[PDB]
Amino acid sequence: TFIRGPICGTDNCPSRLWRIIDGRRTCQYGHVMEGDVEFNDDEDLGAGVITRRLNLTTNATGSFQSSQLTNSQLLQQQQRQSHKKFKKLIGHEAKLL
Amino acid sequence: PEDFQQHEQIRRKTLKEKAIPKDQRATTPYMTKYERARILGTRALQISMNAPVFVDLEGETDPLRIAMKELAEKKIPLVIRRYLPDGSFEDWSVEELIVD
Amino acid sequence: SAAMYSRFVKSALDDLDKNDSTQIGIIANQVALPSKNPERINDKNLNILLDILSSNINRIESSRGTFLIQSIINFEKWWELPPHTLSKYIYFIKILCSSIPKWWQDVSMILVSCFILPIKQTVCHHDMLKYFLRMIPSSMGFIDTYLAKFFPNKNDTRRKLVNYTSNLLKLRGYCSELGFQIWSLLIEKIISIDVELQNELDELDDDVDDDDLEEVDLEDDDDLDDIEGMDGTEEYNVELTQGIKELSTKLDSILTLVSTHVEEQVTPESLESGEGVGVFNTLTTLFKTHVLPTYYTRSIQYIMFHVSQQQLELMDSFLVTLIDISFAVNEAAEKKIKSLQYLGSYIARAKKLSRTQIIFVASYLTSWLNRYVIEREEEVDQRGGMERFKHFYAAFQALCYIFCFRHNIFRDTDGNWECELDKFFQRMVISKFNPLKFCNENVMLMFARIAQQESVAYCFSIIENNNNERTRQQFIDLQSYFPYDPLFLKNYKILMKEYYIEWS
Amino acid sequence: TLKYICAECSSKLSLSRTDAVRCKDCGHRILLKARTKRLVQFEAR
Amino acid sequence: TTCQFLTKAVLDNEREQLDSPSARIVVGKLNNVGTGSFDVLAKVPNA
Amino acid sequence: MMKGSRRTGNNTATTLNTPVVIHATQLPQHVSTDEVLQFLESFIDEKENTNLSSSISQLKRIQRDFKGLP
Amino acid sequence: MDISKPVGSEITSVDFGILTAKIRNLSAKQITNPTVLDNLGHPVSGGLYDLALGAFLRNLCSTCGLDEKFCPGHQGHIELPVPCYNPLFFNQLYIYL
Amino acid sequence: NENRETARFIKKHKKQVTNPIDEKNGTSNCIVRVPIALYVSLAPMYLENPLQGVMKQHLNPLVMKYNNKVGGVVLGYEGLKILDADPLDTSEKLIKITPDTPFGFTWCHVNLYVWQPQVGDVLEGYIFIQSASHIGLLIHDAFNASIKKNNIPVDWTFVHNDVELGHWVDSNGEPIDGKLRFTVRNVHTTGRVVSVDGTLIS
Amino acid sequence: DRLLNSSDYTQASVCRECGSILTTQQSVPRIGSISTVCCRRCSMRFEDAKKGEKIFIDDSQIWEDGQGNKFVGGNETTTVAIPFVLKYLDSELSAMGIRLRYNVEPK
Amino acid sequence: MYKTEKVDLALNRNRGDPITQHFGFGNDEWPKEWLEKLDEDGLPYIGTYVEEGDPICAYFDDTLNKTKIKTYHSSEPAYIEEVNLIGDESNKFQELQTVSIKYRIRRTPQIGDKF
Amino acid sequence: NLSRKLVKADSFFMDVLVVPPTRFRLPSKLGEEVHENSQNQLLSKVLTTSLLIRDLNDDLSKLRVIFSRLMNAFVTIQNDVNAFIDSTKAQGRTSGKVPIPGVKQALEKKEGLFRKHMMGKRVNYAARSVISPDPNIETNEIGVPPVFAVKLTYPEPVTAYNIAELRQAVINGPDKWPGATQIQNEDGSLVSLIGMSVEQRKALANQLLTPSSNVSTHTLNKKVYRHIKNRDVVLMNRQPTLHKASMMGHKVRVLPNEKTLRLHYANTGAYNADFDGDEMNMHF
Ligand SMILES: [Zn+2]
């Protein structure tokens, strides 16, 4: 149930840590980290206007890492031709089949 | 070392003109309920940081209750400095203030 | 063919005068490879590089020649060299850190951090350490902050905590100024290990692990041979294995190695000429400050029990230094009751004590108690509870505990009692304080069954009348803490058998 | 067997993959999940 | 009218003396009413 | 690597530790060799009734230098 | 607050003023690039999110040399090619004109 | 103009008290006495004993290190005097407890004894080592000083112990003994070590 | 307690020359040295050398940021105890061109 | 007290953008212990006690190539009452991407309840 | 003017702007969607016109209509630097409901910065709950639920008189009520107690008076963060705080088996309180 982010110290291990009160972060053995700022906001469709259309998304406890391009896309632009079956390219095995 | 010799000497002389001597001090002989609350706040905050206590803390484990016993025996070594509104001040020790 | 390579570094040496640092960034990179990576430097090309720098360091001192010094400093495993390559590398540090002593700041970061290796592995790490401490006298002040910085973590393995400390005992020998600091750094970090062992230990009934063949476990590790940007969010099974049997041998390995060392350091000639008194001062002024304010702690106060019991001089500065604590006026209560607790169990459990010191103690105690009953009987019947007399009740137990374990000392050929014990104890038990009801139940009933067999004073009628007539909780728990109860440490106990009196 | 229920004619049903969310018998687009034998515990309070 | 008074003070080179309770909470100084209208001083025994 | 964390502790210069200000209050005035010898006799004997015993030894190399020979 | 961390120096008075054009000694950044991101989302140097204005997106700071946990942030200046005035002081320069 | 604008720059870097030579020898007089004024905290634990507190908190960490505000290395302190916060010498002074914490701040005077080398000063010291890169010395048996090669004259040769080190022999055919006399070129505030950069040129 | 000590208490650095919160900086030192806190606009850069009959710097007035720029002077800092919004107040008044000067008179 | 939540996976997707994420699990890329609350189709067993944090349905998205499960976040513990899975009418013959899930929160009389 | 410096007329004019640091200009986000900061939307607009007039200046370097574009630039480089500072002082397009309110509207409102964030703040170590009546606590007391009681803590410094209490507080740990939740060492570093067994907690509890061998921190001592006990104090307030008797100091009385704050009837006149769904804040 641990979530990633930066590395850890407290003289043990570079890994992901354990936040205690959702913005205060501890280690795995009971030593404390410093000042998680925990970006939150209130809702006042209102509160100004929907200004533009920009594709930035939180996925890594805070600032943007999701909706980033050409990094998980190479094995997605070739899955159509490979995974589906009976593609109708069979010319000489069809003479054998 | 030329500026600081004068800038100190101005400062300690200005501070002497605002000190009101013991025979000329004109405020109340009582501890004015805010002096009492801050003395017990400041003394207990010193007792919890290992200041030497001058009273038998008879199994008392509360720093605020220790200072309430030092206040009853006139054992708190603090000094109230009462600022008159031009900055001048009177120094009243805690032992000589009447406690309400 | 080793000379043309020696011209490449000398052609590189004036390239900082050409102001590029271009070919240096391949030379200086080439020596800072890891010591399993075969494109590192060898002992031929090192001596090629070394004395270009031991004769012409006048321009490496610049703001861009700095980086090759890092690669010479962080040239890892550097003590693994043959002596025609090692003692030339030792010669380089003795001039680099004397030409620019901005690098003794940085080289001693490496020297202390390799005290983890054993004694025979760091003969060179201590030679450079002894030397600059004579050369740079302003380095006692900040290599001290490197001793505590590189002390190993307690939940790590066991070779680090036994061999970082052993190389640190080498330091105290050739480093006399940095002494009181050595023992403060060790005694504070035994308690981290000593304290977690009694709460893992059972009750006062003795514990046996039924292991006839003990675990040597010299082979208990591997051989001494010594990511993808993110990882992905993870899950449970941290599985902290507790210090069940690991932290029993961590306190075996260390605290035996300590008292082996002090068996040397106190001796009938260092008490004159060396600092055998000075090791005894730096532990007694570390006794009453560090271990004496700990709670619930066996296994550490055997050290002072082992040092003082070496020589008879050391008892005349520890049986009275303990009374400097346990009868003062300026000291708090619970310091005194824990020290009177130290009083009765040091005198009872130490075999090498002489009877010239027993009634040196036991007369000062009976003088205190009889002086107490003179001045303060009339304060019994007044307002106030019987908790005002915790000092008297602690001292009466501190006296009766001596008689339970050293009663045949107080006799003579006639069977008489020194300090009039049948006249003392018949007088004090029946006093208005009633010291049988307000002291430890087990050791006051231990006293009743013995002082009848010794026919000193009779108190079963008063013990019967006290429990028919009948905060406080942590005051009894000082009266239940016998400090020199027997030991859990399976290897340190062997040296205590020559010193420590058993239950019978 | 993982199953569903047609919300219009109460006909049991199961869907795997390349399978439209419809009732095979009628053509109802709304399916409700059935409950199978699975342990849940309660205090009788 | 926050920036309205702010302009009136910048044009005036004003030294805020930090003695009203609104000026002391802004700068975090202890208030001057009640328990903050006097000082406490510890009388130390050695010369 | 481990000199790069706990860098407020690697500052190690709190208000309990270091003074708030130090001002020179006059012009510095040179002492003689006869006076540093009389000073260091007093300053080392006063601190020989802790810290500072790693720096008294530096003074005892300074004290021996003014009146003797290595 | 901690009571084991006393503070020796306190603020007694606050002077109001105007920053003059000696911002040059203060800020040595001169934020010129109007583009604030790039492709791969990295801060472009000279932009508003430059790394000498404080640590950002798990970068060390250029001037502070510290991560997001310990840098204060630092101020950057925009060169204006003309003296544009101040709308705070405009009604008062309109009187001395 | 800029002939009196720069007084807030140039006067700040001019050390007042230079070092004179002694006994008509040439070696300068660098150990100086300076009076200072401290503003220090005082613990609640040292509140029955205020002078031992100021010594153990603020004065003892300051000795044998370089201080910026005196320009030297603090050798000691003599005549510590807490300034009273009650103008009215006397035994019972009083210092001012801060509002938030139980700590009390006060002013103190004391006289330092700092060691102050400057450029052009001439120092003595026993030679510790010497190589064909530099000479290393210990000033007053405590202070490191290195005389590098580009400040040693050209006409001196390094004799070589041929197996294991060796003398730096001058133009006169004299292997040099310990007690050397050299002139300061620069003083270093590099790390926690104070090192004198010196010369042997005219 | 309810408005400073338990909401946004930050011990911040202030120059005792220009009286500012936001012009201070902790330098990026040598790895064999110690960083300290230094003001920026009180510090004059090292390419402003102007000329015992000559001047020379005592090696501790000179500090560097990680950009490599040396600076001479800019010391005389201390630590005060302010609410953290007073940093956000000072920076959002600099964006109006307004300079707040803080007088740290107990020094 | 009953409450319905509409779990929808066409909420972000444009009408032109093809189908990205799928109810169910993705093989070989596996967190366990989601299978205590959830079933093979990535939908919860009905009758299941949930708390805040507990997974309320799973999905596999093609872009991030991950198995992602939506989490129930309300301080009241509930039981899964009903799970309706909603087919499509406008775009026919397309896979499951709208599921409504009804909870029940049991409400014994607590101190503070107004009668 | 003791510094006797000159009032200069370039105090009215801005040759440079300054940009607030990165921490004061973090990107906004709602839902999970990161936006660009509002302070940067009307600031790069100044930085494009800083570049539009910069290329257009190069046409003047080689030498009508270019002045009609140059004078057009001086209006908008003023009308953008007016928009970075105010928002009604830069009217611009005049289309209604103007966004990016500028650095003045961040300072002026009922919310603003002074009223919402300097004069009043949100605090740590506070709680609130519905209140319930109780004739069985004292009139000066408050009945604290055990939900609140094992959450709010007090940094007690450990000394020679409270080591008996503070050992048992570390042993009881974060779940048994007269307990603790963190210890703070003399270097200011915190050690949490939440994952630990009683053996690691009895390890820490027997080391509270052991002096760490440092010299920087020989003055300091440790701090146990004990829970809230019966001797603690609480400021209670009914929320429309008309007079100062609606914010009084109560003594803590920790009551088992209860989930609401619980108050005596003698205190209901001063808080204007009726026990029908009212809440009161509890500051510690
Ligand atoms: Zn840790």
Image (cartoon, coloured by chain):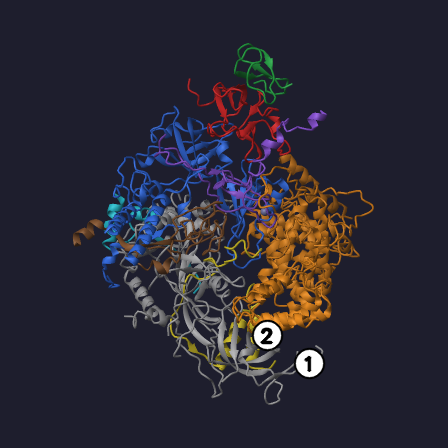
Chain colours: A purple, C orange, D green, E cyan, F yellow, G brown, J red, K blue
**Side of F51 relative to I17 (left or right):** right
Crowding around mark 1 (Cα neighbors within 10 Å: few <14, some 14 to 19, many 20+) is few
Q: Could you tell me which secondary element the residue under label 2 belongs to? A: loop
**Side of C306 relative to C137 (left or right):** right
The alpha-carbon separation of the residues under discs 1 and 2 comes to 19 Å
Quarter in which the C terminus of chain F is drawn: bottom right
Name the residue beneath numbered marker 1: H161
**Is label 1 on the same chain as label 2?**
no
Q: Are marks 1 and 2 in contact (CB under 8 Å)?
A: no
Q: Residue sitting at 69 percent across and 66 percent down?
A: C124
State yes or no: Cβ of the residue under disc 1 lies below 8 Å from any atom of ligand 1. Answer: no
Confirm whether residue J55 shows in the render. Answer: no
Q: Residue sitting at 77 percent across and 43 percent down?
A: C208
Residue C447 picture quarter: top right
Judge whether H191 appears above or below D45 on screen.
Answer: below
Across and down, in percent, residue C299 comes to 69, 51
Q: Residue under mark 2: which chain is it in?
A: C
**Relative depth, front residue between H83 and H92:** H83
Q: Residue under mark 1: which chain is it in?
A: H
**Side of F35 relative to A30 (left or right):** left
Give residue C56's mark: 2
Quarter in which the N terminus of chain F is drawn: bottom right
Crowding around mark 2 (Cα neighbors within 10 Å: few <14, some 14 to 19, many 20+) is some
Q: Amino acid at mark 1?
A: Asn
